[PDB]
Image 1 (cartoon, rainbow, N blue to C red):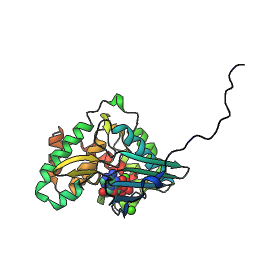
Image 2 (image 1 turned 180 degrees about the vertical axis):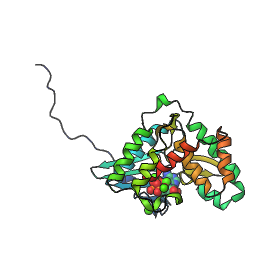
Image 3 (image 1 turned 135 degrees about the vertical axis):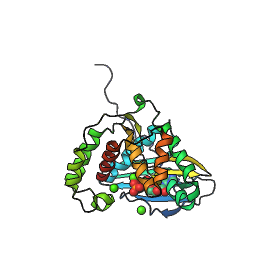
Length: 270
Ligand SMILES: Nc1ncnc2c1ncn2[C@@H]1O[C@H](COP(=O)(O)OP(=O)(O)OP(=O)(O)O)[C@@H](O)[C@H]1O
Ligand SMILES: [Ca+2]
Ligand SMILES: [Ca+2]
Ligand SMILES: [Ca+2]
Ligand SMILES: [Ca+2]
């Protein structure tokens, strides 16, 4: 007809890679993470901010990819690391973000046992804020039907780490956890925007203030107990008093035991 669908041209200028940026940085390997992704802190470069590089391989590559897009979306609502560079190849994902300065909620809870109540109060406020984001803004789905189908896949592929089961399920086969979990069903969904892994090592305090969260790969719409149960579990390692204070400050007098138990068992599959 008139104009050709495609026009022979020359090679466009490509993007500047990691090599141009990462030069001059000192490296430190993270030992905290247990997800399989390799993680490094980049520091010691004058006039440059500290960074984190998270590298996922195989199935973990998908996990890091999921983290990147949820990081990209949620950043408009909550304080998150800034995406500096992301690369996806068929079996690899590299995520370079800004470091959030300070210590995790877990660290400050150990280093300062007397600041426990204050820490919990901040966590509750942060959580109320996260759960106040209008659901209509969230492009990500993390409801129980979705997570369960996901959990079943991880089970059938022998990926579920039984050594990470809670004390109550020490020695249980993954099949028994799966079976018993369904006996708690059903329950009425209370859908909000959730974090997916609202644990003490994912929340960072700096100078007496919670200034951000990380590890946002499971962000999406789910029951509010998806975040509550996990944080409640983490606090149990410290004190039942703090657990109680979390719910009090969040706005719930008495925890829904069934909803609490379901999400705690669900988390065993991930
Ligand atoms: N952007 C960041 N800012 C500050 N600290 C970070 C950042 N990214 C990672 N870290 C540090 O590295 C640790 C591991 O990070 P992350 O939780 O993403 O790894 P993971 O393998 O998913 O860990 P987990 O086994 O808890 O899932 C964190 O506990 C945190 O201390
Ligand atoms: Ca590591
Ligand atoms: Ca983590
Ligand atoms: Ca993680
Ligand atoms: Ca577990």
